[PDB]
Image: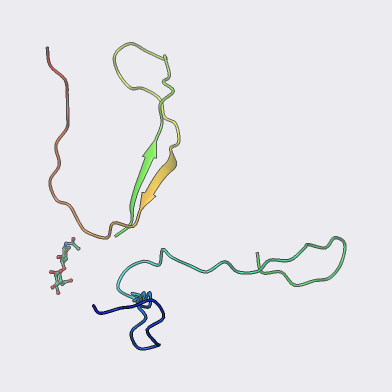
Length: 49
Length: 47
Ligand SMILES: *[C@@H]1O[C@H](CO)[C@@H](O[C@@H]2O[C@H](CO)[C@@H](O)[C@H](O)[C@H]2NC(C)=O)[C@H](O)[C@H]1NC(C)=O
């Protein structure tokens, strides 16, 4: 590579990471953290435990 | 595809040298390996 200190925009090296997600090819192992909430007592409230 | 192992260690000394009695087993490890295995061996130690 030909790079110089402040040589422009197209010559400045950039860090690039490519992420490929595999789905339905195996049991699910990686997941995103779902937001939870506080519980209630003695109230008619539906639940999703 | 799920490989699950149940274990029980505590013995029952009801009789001598034969496994009389019964007791339940509870799972310890579950592995989503997903591939079948038809043959297996065991590892021992000699002297
Ligand atoms: C478990 O057994 C199944 C079928 O008895 C095997 O399934 C085949 O796997 C190959 C992978 O190379 C596929 O190309 C075939 O289409 C599959 N056939 C069927 C009928 O499912 C499998 O290879 C065995 N071993 C494992 C899953 O580790």
